[PDB]
Image (cartoon, rainbow, N blue to C red):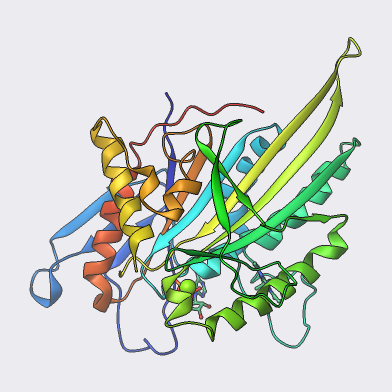
Length: 333
Ligand SMILES: Nc1ncnc2c1ncn2[C@@H]1O[C@H](COP(=O)(O)OP(=O)(O)O)[C@@H](O)[C@H]1O
Ligand SMILES: CC(=O)/N=C1/NN(C(C)=O)[C@](C)(c2ccccc2)S1
Ligand SMILES: [Mg+2]
């Protein structure tokens, strides 16, 4: 098989956009997204697509999590490598979804903030779930940013802020690679996560001021690895290793080698062309497994309601729809 998952999430209007009206309507039950392509004179022309899941503007973070992220976490705990990423135009919610936002004036703890996104939630759930099944386990996390074909580690303490790091192909996995010098931190309890993110958050900032049009132009890849012990009825011991990669892509509005290449790889997979160009960009190289690989991958494509962004929105959905045909064969480690 076995197919990958694509879901669409559309954000609500800004204060700013309030005074417009939407051309996008998502009907979750039917799993469709409809966009009005006509402008002011047609109103009846629509483009509609069907995705595995569709989340409208009414959707809270919690819902997104339960709907797509939870199931994935189950798999990760079983030993699968899972990748989830966000794709969309800038300003449409990728960053929000994957990481979320922290509400102001400590109203909520990090754990209960409802603006929190997938990453922090995921980190939280992991400790809960794992802890609740007894068993020895450990968590390692890493975060890297890819800007302009250069990789920067956001968790490194080093004052060698932008030391480019190097990757090599990994022999153990033919579709994978290792990044030498990438810091991986072992997180021992839920109480250490926030500190990491925050730290990570800061370092990203520095780099922002280290280079041109950052946020919107680079990709961030967050990864968690989990090793859990299990015992069979026969005393044989099992070790499961699972990895979840959560990535926040660069705006689809777009030096952009990683993104282009990605589109290219996708086309190749979908069309069956004999040689697929994973090697052409740093990003595709690390996500090779995800696309046509051994991992289960989910893509969240985020779009916006505003009339203004119609062309981008349409393209975002086109892209998403066609990615639905990638096939992966998920396997357990
Ligand atoms: N589903 C949503 N619900 C509420 N606010 C959202 C949603 N999606 C995006 N936003 C808001 O819109 C702004 C842009 O989102 P951002 O996360 O930066 O998207 P991108 O990474 O695609 O630029 C942020 O202020 C964020 O709070
Ligand atoms: C790599 C990464 O995701 N870094 C983060 N730093 N955060 C801080 C400081 O609030 C985020 C936005 C968050 C949001 C809600 C709840 C908890 C954390 S996520
Ligand atoms: Mg962004």
